[PDB]
Length: 396
Ligand SMILES: Nc1nc2c(ncn2[C@@H]2O[C@H](COP(=O)(O)O[C@H]3[C@@H](O)[C@H](n4ccc(=O)[nH]c4=O)O[C@@H]3CO)[C@H]3CC(O)(O)C[C@H]32)c(=O)[nH]1
Image (cartoon, rainbow, N blue to C red):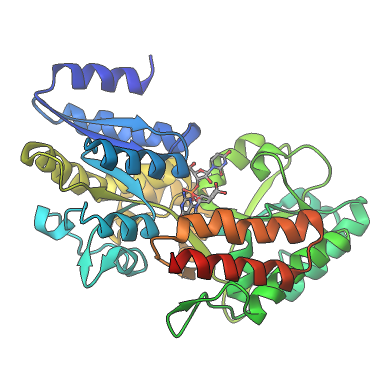
């Protein structure tokens, strides 16, 4: 008997039901969310949260847009920073601090990301950071240290690919993988407030991936998650969301490693991309639904909920107090990867928080990356096209 059943039963008896629309399709993220809600719902009398799976994150924001057009929004939903920006155009979001939710002790990396015109409009919930996944067995077999620099990373991917007879750095040709190389070659998306997809660091980053494919050390993954492709050919490394941790653990037929990202120098790990979502509260919710949202958001920010959620998933605990919780401490003491994920969370960069950014990242930038990697499009030409399509979108 599944948590979503327990929850359906809880909400059946409840006087007030606050819907939480989410983008978790399964595995540990879905189960840890459902587990959190079952615990919250047991402490209420006649008050519940009902989680509603809307598919993936793209499906979720499409369904929220349709909810506005139909005039029936949930109480809460997951949202990226750029989704928050879009919902704020429609004035659709309640300021978090007005609900009475205390945000002292939320990591400033995550809080700064939800603050628009000095006003917090989201509660960091499931915040991920990119990490280096690696094959501990394969690096040991060839006496290869974990690479700490981009230079060591490329040298390691070449050495191991030559040794195993195939490309060992696995990557999706997408905006997220691109962000890692872009950021760590000195790139920035905003130049004097204008969005720039075709800067020389963008050309450099997309060139490095395309050269990695041509040179036989980088393997493009075109069908499924990297962790869904494991077992076909030699794997040494990938740069991927911390929220992949349970997926990689379940799939890997090798000893899985987690490290901090290779940086420009050993002075500091490389910057990871922050992904995952914040919880927003819709103004259209009733006072009674908003009160359930307030208690639910206080629960989600509690040290125990954060300790359980983050240790179940590989998401980053969003509060100072979660790291001081004995349940977090017990898992960390048993598993050095949790500390590795927290350490990487200190070296964190975000994509632009523009309303149009969801469209741009997948349909424009993402497509330019695929053109370059999959169809050998010239990197500059592919990014010049992306820039123009972005400029026309931002004009329209
Ligand atoms: N809609 C929209 N999406 C965005 C935006 N910025 C980034 N992203 C996407 O965030 C995903 C990272 O979010 P995260 O919560 O860290 O991790 C996800 C999953 O990625 C990961 N997962 C799921 C199944 C699996 O087999 N393996 C696995 O790792 O588990 C989590 C819950 O599904 C990336 C993934 C992407 O689909 O390629 C597109 C990326 C945006 O602005 N909008």
